[PDB]
Amino acid sequence: NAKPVYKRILLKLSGEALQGTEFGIDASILDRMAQEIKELVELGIQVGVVIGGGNLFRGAGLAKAGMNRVVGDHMGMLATVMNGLAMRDALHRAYVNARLMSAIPLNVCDSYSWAEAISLLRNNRVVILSAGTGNPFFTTDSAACLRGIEIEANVVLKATKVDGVFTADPAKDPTATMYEQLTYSEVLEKELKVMDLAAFTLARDHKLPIRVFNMNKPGALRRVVMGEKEGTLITE
Amino acid sequence: AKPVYKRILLKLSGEALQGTEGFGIDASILDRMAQEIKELVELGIQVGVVIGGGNLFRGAGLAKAGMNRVVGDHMGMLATVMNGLAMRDALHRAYVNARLMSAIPLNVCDSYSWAEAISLLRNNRVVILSAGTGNPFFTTDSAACLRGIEIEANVVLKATKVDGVFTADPAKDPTATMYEQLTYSEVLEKELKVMDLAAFTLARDHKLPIRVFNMNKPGALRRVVMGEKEGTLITE
Amino acid sequence: NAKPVYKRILLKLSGEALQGTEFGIDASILDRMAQEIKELVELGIQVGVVIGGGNLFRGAGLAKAGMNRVVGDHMGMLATVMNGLAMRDALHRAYVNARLMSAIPLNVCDSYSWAEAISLLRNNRVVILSAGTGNPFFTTDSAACLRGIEIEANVVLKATKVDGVFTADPAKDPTATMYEQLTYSEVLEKELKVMDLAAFTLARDHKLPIRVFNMNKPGALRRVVMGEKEGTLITE
Amino acid sequence: AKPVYKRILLKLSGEALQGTEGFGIDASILDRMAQEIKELVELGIQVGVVIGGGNLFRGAGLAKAGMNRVVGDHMGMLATVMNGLAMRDALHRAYVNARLMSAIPLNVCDSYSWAEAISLLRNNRVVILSAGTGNPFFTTDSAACLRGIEIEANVVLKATKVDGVFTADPAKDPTATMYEQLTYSEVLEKELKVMDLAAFTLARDHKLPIRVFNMNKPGALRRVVMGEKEGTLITE
Amino acid sequence: NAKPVYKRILLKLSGEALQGTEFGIDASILDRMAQEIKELVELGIQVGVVIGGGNLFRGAGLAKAGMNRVVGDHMGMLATVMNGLAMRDALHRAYVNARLMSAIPLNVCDSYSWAEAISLLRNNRVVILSAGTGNPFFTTDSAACLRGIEIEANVVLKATKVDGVFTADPAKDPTATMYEQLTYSEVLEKELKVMDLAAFTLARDHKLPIRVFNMNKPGALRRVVMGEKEGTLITE
Amino acid sequence: AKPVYKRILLKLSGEALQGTEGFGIDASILDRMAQEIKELVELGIQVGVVIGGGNLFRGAGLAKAGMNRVVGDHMGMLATVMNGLAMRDALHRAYVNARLMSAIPLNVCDSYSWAEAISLLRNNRVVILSAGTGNPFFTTDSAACLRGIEIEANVVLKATKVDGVFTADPAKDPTATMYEQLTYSEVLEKELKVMDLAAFTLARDHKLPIRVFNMNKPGALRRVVMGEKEGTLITE
Ligand SMILES: O=c1ccn([C@@H]2O[C@H](COP(=O)(O)OP(=O)(O)OP(=O)(O)O)[C@@H](O)[C@H]2O)c(=O)[nH]1
Ligand SMILES: O=c1ccn([C@@H]2O[C@H](COP(=O)(O)OP(=O)(O)OP(=O)(O)O)[C@@H](O)[C@H]2O)c(=O)[nH]1
Ligand SMILES: O=c1ccn([C@@H]2O[C@H](COP(=O)(O)OP(=O)(O)OP(=O)(O)O)[C@@H](O)[C@H]2O)c(=O)[nH]1
Ligand SMILES: O=c1ccn([C@@H]2O[C@H](COP(=O)(O)OP(=O)(O)OP(=O)(O)O)[C@@H](O)[C@H]2O)c(=O)[nH]1
Ligand SMILES: O=c1ccn([C@@H]2O[C@H](COP(=O)(O)OP(=O)(O)OP(=O)(O)O)[C@@H](O)[C@H]2O)c(=O)[nH]1
Ligand SMILES: O=c1ccn([C@@H]2O[C@H](COP(=O)(O)OP(=O)(O)OP(=O)(O)O)[C@@H](O)[C@H]2O)c(=O)[nH]1
């Protein structure tokens, strides 16, 4: 009798979380991703997914090596388009209707269009938003919040490799602990790592709730949507 | 003792930008490539470059993992655009006029246009050609021979990590010897591995000469262009 | 009780076969074409058609007259887009759902897109692929085999003006005879005229059967699809 | 005795490229046109060219055959792009800077852009304008007067196979005489055939002078531009 | 029992009539517009609407101030795209399927395409045509007649701020009177203000009836469509 | 006494082109702006311009009226393109090379391209950047700081109708005084209104200096660029 507690969601997929040991993409994690997204679609949930590129390139990182920061961000963005393309295909092969859209118009997929996106969602099609915001100096987390506000999602689900928001990187600091609930205020006064002010403040400004969970946990995405104890919730 | 080629078509394998890790791009090797191409431009030579994507993706390889071959080939092509973009930036940072063109419209960079290409070339601007031929079921080798014939290059220079064409792999067999010259017919007869059959065949029909050389041996590119003994030549 | 022996086909239409006495297009042959394609659509067959331009321009021919070979191929390609447009219209007027796609993005029709093409076919829409492969130095026969492999056709039906594959041009050599069956091997050891190695080898490589028939024969296309004795079959 | 026009708009009828066969393009006449335009460019004159498609297709003609008029007009326009492409190549082969622009985006050639056009013109590059006005129910004559007014040409030179404007067809009536000058009003009053009414009317309202001359009479184009007695002038 | 007397109409909306006191747009007039268009859609009528830009910019007017006439027309056109976008949104918010198309390809809406437009109309979607004809020196009235003939409307409904065609501007001349019926002949011999010959003659040429009514009159559009006494009818 | 900035980013508020009426564009102020920018170009300074759209539309303002915020922001952006087009024409009419680029592909003008921008700038061509950042929920101020950082401008010059930054509005309070210099920290601490928080914050992180000055005070722009006491500087 459960029933989902969300009608339209914006699922931000970390690029790094498509690696799963060794750079590149992990086909089996991609296929699991599809199956889990398939379930949401059937449950009637409208899904829009913003995907990152950290498993291939990060602009700032390339900038340290000497490259022009803008060109570095452009490669980072093309990296998100490569993930989006792999994700879409995994979706099609799992018999799920999906469309890839790119912030920077390319031709291989559609160009992002607001009205078109809303139409696709109302029609139960999964919409994959690539190239983030289309601009350099930004991160895909920003795009998740922007697109999330544009398509009017009920919430942004940040898929990560950790169970929630920790006080410090749980993989490097042995003192790291995660909270299960936070307000946009607490996040700043405690200075916990969630996103980057740019993205965050935008979400706060527009009162868009955020739920941080672990995508490496099979079933976690479904628990979040069904309203079961998973991850951390950031509200006002 | 001036150069022997007015216009060439440099074909770099995606692995050419790989560091010691065996994947991605290595800033220092990129910058080194840019200096070597800078010298050719100053020498009066017109340069067109076709770069691969093996340091990132291969369609056949992805298809084995379950993915749709065509989508795998699109990601491969897209990777060659990531390389072309990094190569262009190294060029601009070394003060060399260069323009990235793509066989797949990506209005990042502009689209490949034969007429525009010939114009950029006549103006001493290095033309970088990404996305191979624009179609799946093809390799960047074929794009090198194709573009090479379109822009009327004097020769296709195939960059490898070996000094030339051997009787067998010299690293997996110390008996192997390097040919100083060959005809398309002998390559096929002796079952020699130079490049993709489709591509090779194309170059043979249009009598486009091929020079296989070592891009890691300092001075090689210049020597190959100065008519000095270096690598293997292939004609007929 | 017949029932078609093919579910998805790639129909390669020769440009020359739309002339029918006197250059240009033959409206009545175009309308018959539509009616016959209409029948396949109703039978449930998914049709993708690659159309040539030989009735208007051929690149190599223009090259002999002195023109730049690449520009010549570009005109040849625009010629296929003109035929595709006429074909599409004949289809619409016969109340058949059809979409025109061009290898070289134009705007008047759609730009070729793999995923989009598959969706249109699954939806029983006729897909007309123009501008061949998008590249010069190639022929539309190449494109028929490439697109045929891309959309995963069960077979490529080469529509011609002769009943099959002959030993020599039946219109010029009085010794010309046609075979009714051939393997990709036989085709080469006998050196019979079918396509051009480029195209052919590709088809062979991917084990795509080919059936050569005469489109000037009213009903021939329907016989081929129903599995009746028509034309020549090339298999491995 | 320098030229009398700084910038002109040469309007070539599609038939201007037709050989003796009465269809298509004749390489030798094309090359001859290129030499005559080369001379004008050297003389300091800025040249814009609008070419028709009657040596290939006409929308009204196709519509009579059953086809949708709009589609017929698209094919007609597309033919003017085939001519513009061949004319551009003859130009480049005669060493004349020229760029083909299209009223129908064909990202082959680039799109018509008024500002870019004026810039190319000021840079002594022959601008070739294809696809007429971009809309059906119009002729390339109207595009000649329209573009002529946009680029602020000093005059529209209408190339015909006759010496000028006659009282009646001189080939179907030996009584006919050639006017050396006329006003838009007299043309309409005497029911004289100069061009499409829509087009004519447009030129009259913007006071764009028209010179009708013979493109086959050697030296004519130069004479018309050197203020020497040649053809018919039309103003008011 | 009424029943509409038209199946497909082309509704030309004056840009000025979206102001309603004070430049800019009048949201409440826009919402009424939507409701009235909603009714037509439900009645089964296929609606195509051409919208002007006179409430923001007029090319000729900008030309007097000193600006380049062509650039002035380009701004006028962008003005029609801004109105089209506002109109579309008002339509979506009233739960009416609508698509915006632009004569000059932009990316934010679709690019105008004939076949696509017809498909959208057959599917009961409202089609908004912006950027008029795409060319300078023309008015949106021209585009209304051109698009009207293209999509094969049964009639063009010119929405204005006056009840019909008057002898003189009813707001400035106290002698102004309107006729209730006119032939294309009468319109010229009486020289009444309806459109501009360009547009008009085109409509006449193609025998497209025109009905001029007042959109500020709530219900007037519905009366016209139902065949009730409203506005002025221009026929041959 | 040469200029103190090699490359600047001039940000003009849409209201900067407004006449006394309080809406639209005033030809004379436009021409005056062009003369002031002409002088900078002659002085060797590279100029990038980001113009707003408040003299026409604001998304938030439209959203209050009932419209979809995103669509309101698209119309706003589109208005900045109307201004950019008028500003470009005034520039060309004053004989200043200038190119309009848009963050929203409008193939009127070409699309924004970082690399192309840097090239135009190095060539002494004024680059006009329209459509802000390309995304809704942003202001042109943010686009000024963003583009300013991308093109590596030496400073962002914020044109206002006031002499600089005051303690309070000087027109609504005669006690207000003008700061001659400030740090990002003091602006935020003293609750000073300089620009959009999002934008400001961005400029602070990249240490992009901001100069607020009066665009109506003749000579101001030149003085600001000649290192002479004028307006308010903001750095840290
Ligand atoms: O709006 C955007 C989004 C992305 N990008 C560029 O794409 C690159 C991809 O970086 P992402 O931020 O997409 O990486 P990711 O999601 O995998 O990383 P985490 O969430 O785990 O931190 C970024 O480093 C940036 O340079 C932009 O330039 N603009
Ligand atoms: O025309 C093209 C070119 C390339 N590709 C796609 O790019 C992928 C990378 O293949 P490449 O041919 O780009 O590899 P590479 O140059 O780095 O490697 P070498 O052959 O030099 O050893 C291919 O596996 C394919 O998926 C296309 O599908 N089409
Ligand atoms: O991939 C392609 C396809 C076509 N083309 C160009 O289009 C032209 C049209 O030539 P086609 O090969 O399309 O002609 P056709 O089908 O009518 O001829 P047959 O099958 O009967 O032999 C060719 O001559 C070539 O120049 C390309 O450049 N590339
Ligand atoms: O604006 C345009 C121009 C041309 N066309 C299309 O191009 C076709 C060719 O008509 P053209 O007007 O191009 O013919 P032409 O110049 O060769 O012939 P003359 O008038 O000089 O005798 C026309 O019949 C129409 O279908 C358009 O529809 N729109
Ligand atoms: O085909 C076209 C249409 C429109 N435009 C340009 O758009 C501008 C908008 O002018 P319109 O003619 O669209 O204005 P309107 O409809 O509001 O005015 P009325 O019907 O009440 O007279 C025109 O002034 C012109 O410069 C073109 O350049 N070409
Ligand atoms: O990135 C952008 C820029 C602008 N806009 C849209 O443009 C509208 C106009 O807002 P602007 O920010 O262009 O206004 P302006 O410069 O004239 O005004 P000041 O801030 O200088 O006082 C905004 O209200 C928004 O709708 C975007 O949505 N995105």
Image (tube, coloured by chain):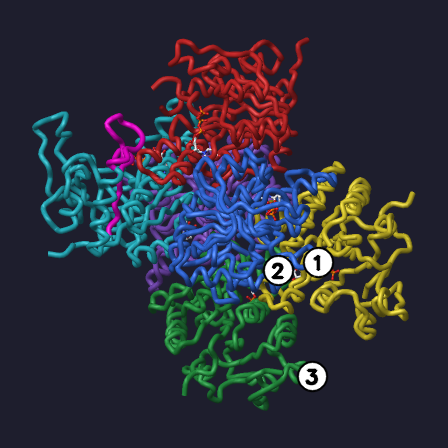
Chain colours: A yellow, B blue, C red, D cyan, E purple, F green
What's under tag 1, amino acid-wise?
Glu
In magenta stretch: residue B44: no
Residue B5 visible from this viewpoint: yes
- Say if disc 2 is inside 8 Å of ligand 6: yes
**On the image, which quarter does residue F233 sit in?**
bottom right
What's under tag 2, amino acid-wise?
Pro
Q: Residue at x 33, y 36 (%)?
A: E184
D210 horizontally vs D77: left or right: left
Residue B110 visible from this viewpoint: no
For marks 2 and 3, the one nearer the N-term is 2
Q: Secondary structure at mark 2?
A: loop
Quarter the C terminus of chain B occupies: top left
In the image, E137 versus D100, the foreground residue is D100
Mark 1 packing: few (<14 Cα in 10 Å), some, or many (20+)?
Answer: few
In the image, D75 versus C170, the foreground residue is C170
**Residue B91 percent coordinates (x, y):** 51, 62
Q: Which mark is residue F189?
A: 3
- Say if disc 3 is inside 8 Å of ligand 6: no
User: What segment carries the magenta color?
Assistant: D8-29
Q: Secondary structure at mark 3?
A: helix
**Residue E173 percent coordinates (x, y):** 34, 54
Q: Is residue F20 above or below residue B54?
A: below
Residue with the mark numbered 1:
B21
Q: Chain of mark 2?
A: F
Badge 2 vs badge 1, beta-carbon distance below 8 Å:
no
Whether discs 2 and 1 lie on one chain: the answer is no
What's under tag 3, amino acid-wise?
Glu
